[PDB]
Length: 157
Ligand SMILES: NC(=O)c1ccc[n+]([C@@H]2O[C@H](COP(=O)([O-])OP(=O)(O)OC[C@H]3O[C@@H](n4cnc5c(N)ncnc54)[C@H](OP(=O)(O)O)[C@@H]3O)[C@@H](O)[C@H]2O)c1
Image 1 (cartoon, rainbow, N blue to C red):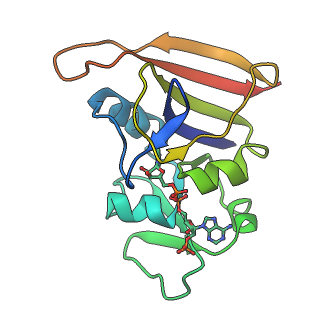
Image 2 (spheres, rainbow, N blue to C red):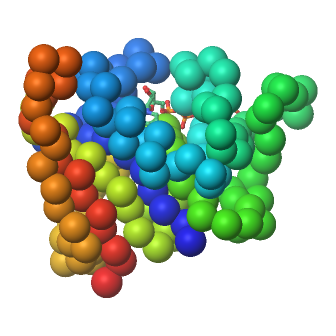
Image 3 (tube, protein in one colour):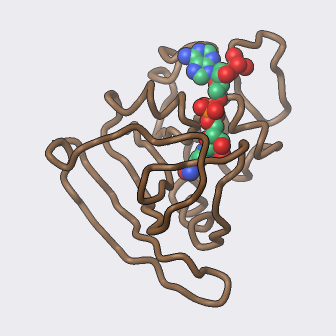
C-alpha cells in the first residue's frame, strides 16, 4: 500500500521555513502511530528539518545527492525507486514529494489543521469527487493541543 501522510491547514499550508507552522503534539503522535513498523519516504529538505531518522520504522530519503549516506537512513534517487519499497509505504513530504505522488498513491492520511497559518509550502489542491472519506475523526483539544484538527483517511475513488 502506498499512502500520503500529511497535515495541512484550511488553505493547504504544510510548512514555513522548513518547519511545521504549528505546534500540535497529538498530530506527531498520530504520525508515530500510523508509520511505526512501516516505511516513511521523505524529500531531502524534510529530512534535514527532522535531522535524524524517526525511530522504529524504515526511513527513506529522496535526493539527487549521490554523496548522501546517513546512518539509519536508506537513500533513493528517483521517484521510480519508491515502487520497489516493500510493505506499507507512507509519502511523508515535503511539497515536492506530495506533488509528485498525489496522483499515484492509493490513499491519504490527512490531518486538517482548522486554522490559517503563514506558509511557504503547500499541499496540492485535490477534490472530494476523487476521494472517498473512509473516516473523519475530530482531534481532541487540551492544554498542549489547542488548534482544532480533523483526522481524515481518504481513499481514491
Ligand atoms: N505538514 C506536513 O505534514 C509536512 C510533512 C513533511 C514536511 N513538511 C514541510 O514541507 C516543507 C518542505 O517541502 P519542500 O518541497 O521544500 O522540500 P522536500 O520535498 O522535503 O525536499 C525537496 C528535495 O527532495 C529531493 N527530491 C524531491 N523529488 C526528487 C526527485 N524526483 N528526484 C531526486 N530528488 C528529489 C530533492 O533533494 P535534493 O535537492 O538534495 O536533490 C529536493 O530538493 C518543509 O517546510 C516541511 O516542514 C510538512
